[PDB]
Amino acid sequence: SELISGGWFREENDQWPGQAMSLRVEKVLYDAPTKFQHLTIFESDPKGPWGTVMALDGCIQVTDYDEFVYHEVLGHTSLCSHPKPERVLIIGGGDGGVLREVLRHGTVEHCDLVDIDGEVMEQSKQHFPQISRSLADPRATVRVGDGLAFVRQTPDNTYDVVIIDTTFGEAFYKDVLRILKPDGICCNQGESIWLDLELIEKMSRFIRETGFASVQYALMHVPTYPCGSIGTLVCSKKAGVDVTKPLRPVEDMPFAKDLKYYDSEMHKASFALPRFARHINN
Amino acid sequence: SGGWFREEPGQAMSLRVEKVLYDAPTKFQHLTIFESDPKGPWGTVMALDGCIQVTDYDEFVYHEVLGHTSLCSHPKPERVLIIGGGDGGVLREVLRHGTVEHCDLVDIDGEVMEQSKQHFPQISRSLADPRATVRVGDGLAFVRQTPDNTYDVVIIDTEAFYKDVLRILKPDGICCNQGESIWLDLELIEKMSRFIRETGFASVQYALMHVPTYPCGSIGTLVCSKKAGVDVTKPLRPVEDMPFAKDLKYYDSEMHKASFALPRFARHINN
Ligand SMILES: C[S@@+](CC[C@H](N)C(=O)[O-])C[C@H]1O[C@@H](n2cnc3c(N)ncnc32)[C@H](O)[C@@H]1O
Ligand SMILES: C[S@@+](CC[C@H](N)C(=O)[O-])C[C@H]1O[C@@H](n2cnc3c(N)ncnc32)[C@H](O)[C@@H]1O
């Protein structure tokens, strides 16, 4: 009801006030409130590199340009930290990007994807076909529902990996821990080390107190995020496992040469944090 | 416009202006200095020709990376040259090294350092250091009039020029320059990298850093070596052995190594 072709999309929020990042709108493809959140999709300036942009509640979540960074990091940092990931769960990820990356792994026999907003996937199918192609994969079962409810009703020792593609109390992470198998790996999108370092520390310790043996924060270069860097918490249920070094190097996989960001050297480097934030990983 | 500093094709990044401390064209460029929103973390902001160059918040990232990645790649950096860096941030980091006996800093705009003294006192403090000699002049002209084998490290905080940089460096000399973004101008990085190599430098490696104020949230630096067989991607001398290691807010040896791991789309820059 607002965004007009030729106008400018303006991203801005609290926690980080007195700052704004704006993108020119070439064409508004979708702009309306869904049952759960406000979904905005528009074509960015053709002379710029971003292409099609998706925003949720005013926050950019997907762009054609840097899309691969976040999806490869979440998908591969987690699965390459697992001895043999066969059954995988994705909470959120309706766009299908993380799913696409998880499906590259031949070890994966099945992946369950549970996103609460069915309109996110519908609009992703229409305006991000190269990302959402994964949603129709035989090895994928896509559910439209709450992930909190899903994990609570999932039996013990079901999944090898749980990827939480959504920025969720203690009952939820207790559920994530219990639904994972003994060598299970949990993955969540973490906050920025710049605009909310304090919440990362809290989330990191809270996840460990829930029962997970270890948690490590991985950093990534994603240009569309306010400070140009989001991260991801890679947690481990099993004790005595170092997720900072690739358990199975992706170079041994055939799809290794198809990735645009991730490789074993990026994996290692992602867990190297600036001195001011180093204490998170110790 | 109304209490909002905007930067830059079909995109823009804006900051609210709490108080304008300085805004005028100098002899060489337009210098803007303002206090950002107090409820935000940026603090005092400096922009040159509309481009943010220094903010209180992330200032340390760029200055530590340029200063320490270069010096920690040198066996014994005693004489150092800094072209640009009038704010004094890189100089401050260079001066942390006890091996450094002298540092020459040459910035073309004297008003940049004057305004840095006033509005960035904790950064520009280094400019008055005994081991520092600060010159107001063109670095192109300076390096061409500098004798051969003068410096251990040259930091460019900004063909005849890089020929001069190569010549004025001693045999195990290390050159450092600010590189472009791997996102918004990857093609220029490759050109610059090859061009520096064909000038005569044995090796060149691009280091990546997390700097939140830059358009895409990541600028980089080219660290180049005059001597062949030198791998700058691993610290020659870990900073952990120096007494100032714990004073650094960004740089350490693990970050040093991590900085040269590039995304696959940009890996051809480092081979
Ligand atoms: C669009 S993705 C954001 C990831 C993005 N790539 C980024 O950089 O952060 C977030 C998705 O999580 C979903 N989601 C939000 N709350 C949820 C919940 N409680 N259960 C399951 N999915 C949820 C939303 O529908 C949304 O599509
Ligand atoms: C402020 S620094 C930029 C570094 C900054 N920390 C950043 O984030 O990119 C740029 C300085 O280089 C100086 N400069 C520009 N051209 C120069 C030249 N030809 N010779 C010496 N200094 C020059 C400018 O006067 C300016 O002070």
Image (tube, coloured by chain):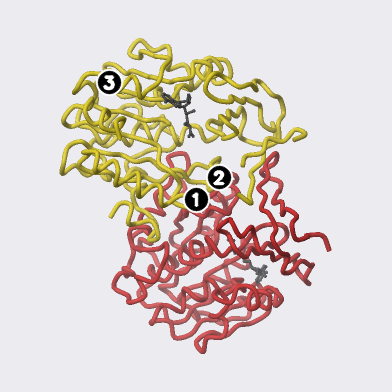
Chain colours: A red, B yellow
Q: Nearer the viewer, residue A189 or B229?
A: B229
Amino acid tagged 1: Leu
- Location of the N terminus of chain B by quadrant is top right
Report the Cα–Cα distance between label 2 and label 1: 9 Å
> Is the shortest distance between ligand 2 and the CB of mark 1 under 8 Å?
no
Image position of A250 (left or right of A128): left
Whether pointer 2 and pointer 1 mark residues with C-beta atoms closer than 8 Å, the reply is: yes
Q: Which mark is residue B215?
A: 2
Label 3 belongs to which residue?
B100
Label 3 secondary element: loop
Type of amino acid at the residue the image marks with label 2: Pro
Q: Quarter-wise, where is residue A164 in the image?
A: bottom right
Q: CA distance from mark 3 to mark 2?
A: 34 Å
Mark 2, secondary structure of its residue: loop
| Quarter location, residue A123 | bottom right
- Mark closest to the chain's N terminus, 2 or 1: 1
Residue drawn at the location 67% of the way across and 57% of the way down: A59
Specify the quadrant that holds the C terminus of chain B: bottom left
